Image 1 (cartoon, helix red, strand yellow):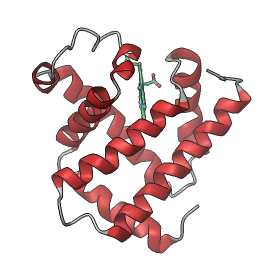
Image 2: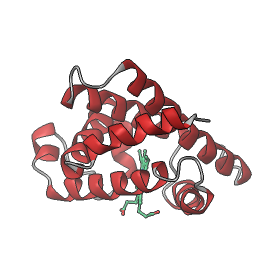
Image 3: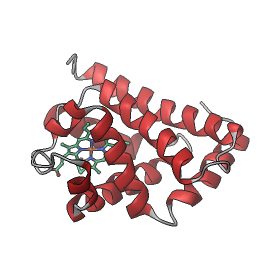
Amino acid sequence: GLSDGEWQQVLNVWGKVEADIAGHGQEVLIRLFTGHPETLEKFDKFKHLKTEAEMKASEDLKKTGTVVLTALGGILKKKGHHEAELKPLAQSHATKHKIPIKYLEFISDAIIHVLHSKHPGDFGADAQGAMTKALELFRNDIAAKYKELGFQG
Ligand code: HEM
């Protein structure tokens, strides 16, 4: 999917996320959750959250943001060589959590969103470029694993 000039850009950018993994992860789930409320319903431990103050105020969400961004970061550093790390992922979201690929689209968008909000002006057009393709490659490989499982819905 990507050139290493592009990989280069992705890890450049992930350097931003790693300086504050907990904050980045919190705002991603908040951007996910507030924009597409049906997504909250897939989490039984965040179901109670009703307002953004509550989410904001929730320590368990900051926690889940770190797990999520820690796992993706683990995949991105593989530079597309991630069958081993993604299968387990795709299996769990399809069979156990029942997560529609559309939701993986929403969170992909939510990361691009967040990044511009936290780093206005230092999230280059080129960087957006690389990051979007990287998220697409991630999403595409999951989509395939999802097809195998007939995880239609
Ligand atoms: C970049 C995308 C994502 C990554 C890297 C990610 C990562 C993870 C990891 C590492 C776990 C725990 C281990 C496991 O169950 O496999 C997990 C659990 C879970 N994920 Fe995701 N996830 C992603 C997207 C999503 C989305 C979009 C949703 C729903 C809109 C979601 C819903 C859940 C749920 C419900 C669980 C179980 C939560 C619990 O522990 O109670 N995930 N995810």
